[PDB]
Image (spheres, helix red, strand yellow):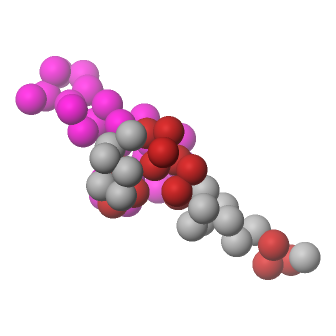
Amino acid sequence: IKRKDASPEQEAIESFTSLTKCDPKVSRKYLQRNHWNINYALNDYYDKEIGTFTDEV
């Protein structure tokens, strides 16, 4: 149900995908890992993409 501004998905996906600079379909696969909880899904994504920063340490 698109609310002409933020779908039930886009209220997490567009907030997530803009905060993580990824593609909207990637937010959709870290949200589906955390029952579309944007806080839990952000820690999991920062555990997969940002959790490997030590590649120069």
Is 18 magenta? The answer is yes
| Residue sitting at x 39%, y 40% | 37
- Residue 9 image offset from top left, x and y in percent: 24, 39
- Over which residues does the magenta segment extend? 1-28
Does any portion of residue 14 appear in the rendered image?
no
Query: Which of the pair 16/39 is nearer the observer?
Result: 39
The percent coordinates of residue 42 (x first, y second) are 52, 47
Rendering coords of residue 55 (x, y %):
79, 78
Quadrant that contains the C terminus: bottom right
Q: Quadrant of residue 12?
A: top left
Instruction: Pick the residue in front: 18 or 31.
Output: 31
Compared to 50, does 8 lie above or below? Answer: above
Q: Residue at 43% of width from left, 39% of height from top? A: 38
User: Which residue is pictured at 60% across the width and 62% down the height?
Assistant: 47
Query: Any magenta on residue 15?
Result: yes
Q: Is residue 9 left or right of residue 17?
A: left
Quarter of the figure that contains the N terminus: top left
When the figure is inspected, residue 27 is found, relative to residue 39, above or below; the finding is below
Q: Quadrant of residue 7?
A: top left
Closer to the camera in the image, 51 or 21: 51
Residue at figure coordinates x 21%, y 32% from the top left: 8
Left or right, residue 26 beside residue 7: right
